[PDB]
Length: 90
Ligand SMILES: CN[C@@H](C)C(=O)N[C@H](C(=O)N1CCC[C@H]1c1nc(-c2cccc3ccccc23)cs1)C1CCCCC1
Ligand SMILES: [Zn+2]
Image (cartoon, rainbow, N blue to C red):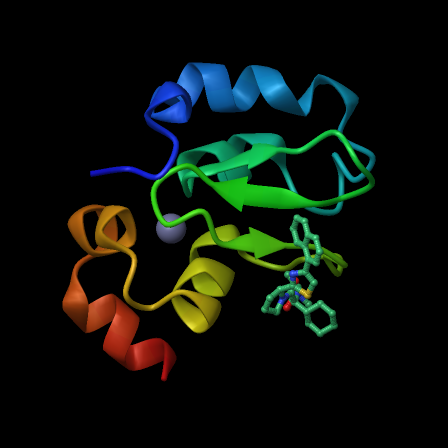
């Protein structure tokens, strides 16, 4: 199951980005959709399912792409995007 079941709701994840410092650069909507919640410190986020953390986001970074790049074994990623998507990023 998920590492952090309490953040399984996309809406709750989205709410966590109220203080996100990079709204124009990396949309909270896309981050939340990709399983990420905001830790509250800087631009650090974490996936609710695999608990993978990502920081130092660059403008135009795609949350789903980054999820697959760094945490290809995440089952939420797999269920959401499929194996073909993950394979093509590598
Ligand atoms: C350019 N696009 C971004 C999204 C990206 O690729 N970030 C990578 C990343 O966050 N990584 C690479 C794998 C692990 C993770 C990291 N995670 C942390 C980290 C350390 C300590 C506490 C943390 C808390 C929350 C999230 C990440 C944390 C540091 S680096 C990495 C950042 C540093 C420079 C190389 C790339
Ligand atoms: Zn994940």
